[PDB]
Image (tube, rainbow, N blue to C red; front, side, top):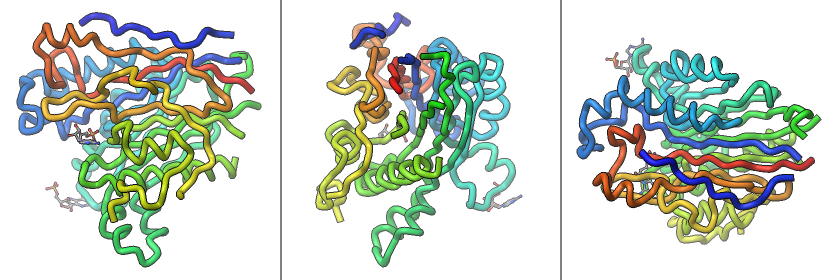
Length: 324
Ligand SMILES: Nc1ncnc2c1ncn2[C@@H]1O[C@H](COP(=O)(O)O)[C@@H](O)[C@H]1O
Ligand SMILES: Nc1ncnc2c1ncn2[C@@H]1O[C@H](COP(=O)(O)O)[C@@H](O)[C@H]1O
């Protein structure tokens, strides 16, 4: 495995810090049926978890957003290992309201945010359950109830205090994992709108910089990305299949095609994971760029996971500069 290159975009000098966003691929969906091209011994969680940890540890981000973190893995692996490195963390599973055995409850995945206690102090934590937000806002709309409310997805957010010696300063970090099905671009879009307006809100109760990490399951051309990038989208955008605006001014850390793919499978490759930040308060100094395509080609790797790549997503990592 060759080092992915750093791509520097702006020079320093304010407070700099790094953010990692990584979908880890939970054990429950790591099957031969979905990943036929990868040996069982390399799919097995005992094997893959080492690679996942190594990835996270060596990125050594100040802020880590993870998706597809298994509940029991959060308590017995991610959190104790990352505490050992100076982090604290917040986790919520999906399906909290769903009835299931204790066994099944250990295996349910969710979203985690972690942060260096040396650099940040946790002030507030929130969980946003898209099913419940959909139901409370259905309004005699049949699509909402049948299509959105039936999707079990979530987002989490923390309010953090940025330690003044890095320059009472606040930062909101939000992590989400939208529904995956490309037949459901409307759900993806609506889940994004609910997430953004639920975040605008957290922002009221406690003008405050925002970092948004997500597995959006949406291409850069999509209505969801259009909506996050341009502050709004038209109510008749084709992605709704069946103008809406937001208050933030956000940019993608990796915009203008810096990676060709974040998710990498035999059947599908493209950019679907993102780190967005509020441009009024921050710049990107740099990003961790793509794994070298020659290396993948030379090693005959057209899908992940693989023995040297422990997930079917690649991590994103960005350095940002924050101003008061
Ligand atoms: N301890 C439990 N609490 C709640 N539901 C349970 C429990 N045990 C079994 N169930 C129900 O039985 C289904 C299958 O259980 P299991 O065979 O243990 O996976 C679960 O999805 C639940 O609907
Ligand atoms: N925008 C999209 N277009 C086509 N397929 C997608 C898209 N987003 C997700 N997928 C599919 O869903 C998978 C991502 O699942 P997840 O692990 O939830 O991100 C991809 O590997 C594709 O199979």
